[PDB]
Amino acid sequence: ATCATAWSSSSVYTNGGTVSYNGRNYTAKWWTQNERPGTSDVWADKGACGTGS
């Protein structure tokens, strides 16, 4: 139901930009280029991602 678009290295994100990864959802704080979310302070888990596998 609710889940941000999975992170995309081919799509620069910015403040407010939300995405999904590792089953959770990450939210950036400002302009950021292709970078592994969760490993950098840039991306922070703002919840969980709902999906079926």
Image (cartoon, rainbow, N blue to C red):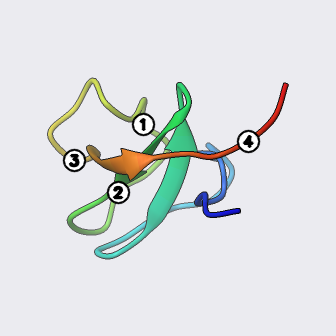
Amino acid bearing label 3: Val
Q: Residue furthest left?
A: 41
Query: Which numbered disc covers residue 7?
Result: none
Q: Which x, y percent locates residue 52?
A: 81, 34
Task: Return the disc, 3 or 4, that comes first in the chain's sequence.
Answer: 3
Q: Are marks 3 and 2 in contact (CB under 8 Å)?
A: yes
Q: Secondary structure at mark 1?
A: loop
Q: Which mark is residue 32?
A: 2
Q: Tell me if mark 4 has few (under 14), some (14-19) or many (20+) residues whose alpha carbon lies within 10 angstroms of its own.
A: few
Counting residues from the start of the chain, the first of labels 3 and 2 encountered is 2
Q: In the displayed image of the protein, which residue is found farthest to the right? A: 53
Counting residues from the N terminus, which is met first, the one under dot 4 or under dot 2?
2
Q: Which mark is residue 42?
A: 3
Q: Is residue 17 left or right of residue 7?
A: left
Q: Which mark is residue 35?
A: 1
Whichever of callouts 4 and 1 sits on the residue coming sooner in the sequence is 1
Residue at horizontal 62 percent and vertical 43 percent from the top: 9
Judged by depth in the image, the label closer to the viewer, 3 or 4, is: 4
In the displayed structure, 36 sits above or below 24; it is above
Do callouts 3 and 1 mark residues in contact (Cβ within 8 Å)? yes
User: Left or right: 36 with respect to 51?
Assistant: left
The image shows residue 16 at horizontal and vertical percentages of 33, 76
Residue flagged by tag 4: what amino acid is it? Answer: Thr
Q: Are marks 4 and 2 in contact (CB under 8 Å)?
A: no
- Which of the 4 quarters of the picture holds residue 18? bottom left
Query: Which quarter of the image is occupied by the C terminus?
Result: top right
The three-letter code of the residue at mark 1 reads Glu
Q: Which mark is residue 51?
A: 4
- State the SS at label 3: loop
